[PDB]
Image 1 (cartoon, helix red, strand yellow):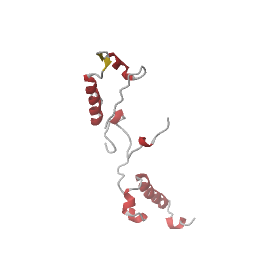
Image 2: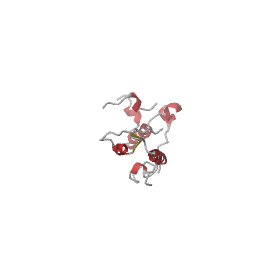
Image 3: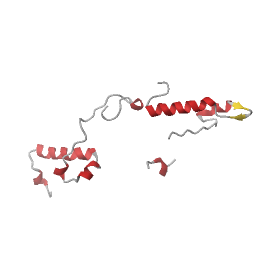
Image 4: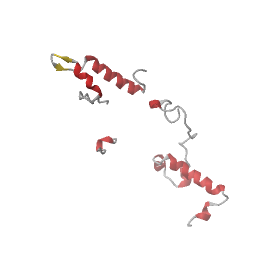
Length: 61
Length: 67
């Protein structure tokens, strides 16, 4: 890895990866109609983490 | 919390910090006001500290000029 031009200065964005090594691998279990879907509560966790970062606290806090 | 809010990112709450960083006698050192704001606080303090160090030895800094 080498830095790019966008790493330097000039909102929150989350990447949902369902691959095995990815921490979000469990999402592949939530399948409805045979097509995987992001859980309705999945957005809630993302927004909760974003607000927690905005305030400066952890989610459990 | 002079520098940043204490406990940020889980950092230790205690650390040694100078009393004030926003002071500088620019007119003495021939620095225009615009450049004084954009100057590093380390350099702003170090100019004064160096002048104090030179005189602290009883040596007028003019004697060292040109050496």
